[PDB]
Image 1 (cartoon, rainbow over the protein chains, first blue to last red):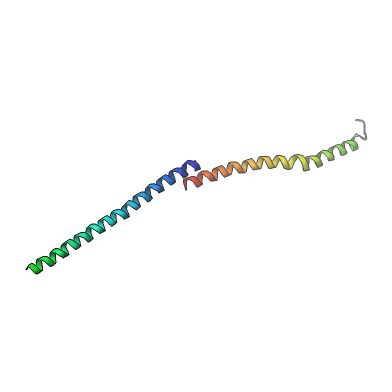
Image 2 (image 1 turned 120 degrees about the horizontal axis):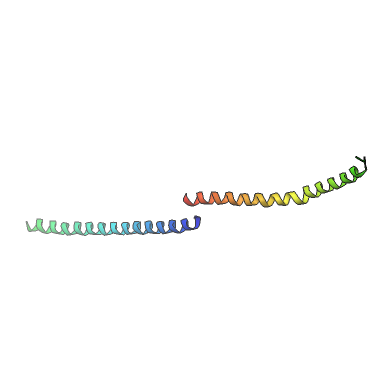
Length: 52
Length: 52
């Protein structure tokens, strides 16, 4: 019962660490999406105001 | 019945079997039982530790 418990605990922990690592990389994908859209509307704001 | 010196020779036989039983027989037997009782108790503790 102690041996089997160790194996699942490890299996559970490895799953939890995998989802947490995915969520931080998904957060960096959200960051880089937000930053590229910010850059995209900053160039577009300048170009419209000078055109104006 | 016959009042007899067998009372004295049997008192030597009695004492010598209690000294050898006290030293040699009883400490090793109780060691073996109580060591098994500890193993069973460590089994109980191990189950609780697994679920913790």
